[PDB]
Length: 213
Length: 246
Image (cartoon, rainbow over all chains, first blue to last red; front, side):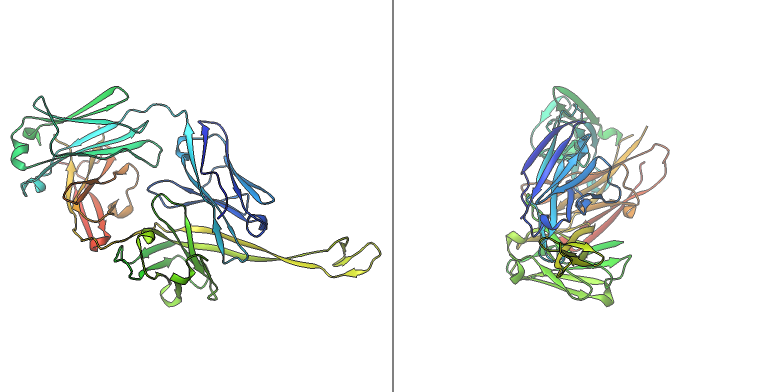
């Protein structure tokens, strides 16, 4: 395995470097590649042949090599660059390959971003099965933490609620979901339900009324 | 160019995990094809590759369990991992691989290439040195296929439309009550990617998962239908749900 730093960090709009150390028989042989891994996406080839950029790769990604150490340098960091970076090289034949241990790149100094919240009522089709799921979708928030409160006719609901942890989107912001699982009768018995999402001291409220859905 | 993995997304322990990769856009006898996997929270792990002549590279640590085969008539490459365990639960990626070998000729201690031969200070002809430079890198990645090595049961999801009550229109699909993970969602058979957002699933105490995919579209789309395509590979199920805002 090629030696990479487990973790590396840089600030927004600045420059960072990730190294990749091997031996004469891999990195020293002089044809190192670099790959980018974002959650929810397949690996992306960034660099090949030490220095060449693959199709669609911005100029601010650059590679180089000195003896048995290769370097991926990213200038003008953006939030979307937060990701896992891997190097690779052939080993003793063009058919035998070695990957690096990987480096997680964190981008510091990202601005605060409030959550976009959508509340969906149960569909008619689900109601026909005597089930009613209210779906609260929460996206595009940074940093990655929200708190969710459900309400109905002025009273807070806790039972039959399920809320996911925050997960990182492809654009570096975060997303999360909350589900209120009721029976059709429960759903019809109230005048309104609300999803209330708090993030960094700010609150967003969305509401549905069975008499309007 | 398209690489599409296929095969059981659910494998019972100790059985042989097997996968197939079907290519298009190129002939399999023209490019090297290979397999790389990633288990959750771990590094990329090269499994192997096979070239046009049958030249095969295998992960040295896993070679005894791996089998990679080629079928040019069907433009297919196969992977097999014998005696599957939990360590083999991972996303398996089919890959196209650039392979090349360079023969490098150089002159030994104290000589230079005057003309074509390595000649020393006195002009005596000397034998050259031959070394090789090896080129390997992945130039095309498949979408990947998540394989889980467990004895889990199977329940296919119900799919319900998500639409707001009554300027941009927001809609989606609720993929309700399935197991095991994962489920994949596209919109309009992949033609609609802009504005899509598919959320990680929630887990009920019943053991069943649910997740939602939503899409935001311009308001000038009244009357239009948008179809979410949901795949539950573990149950070999695929559901298309047409959603039209009311």
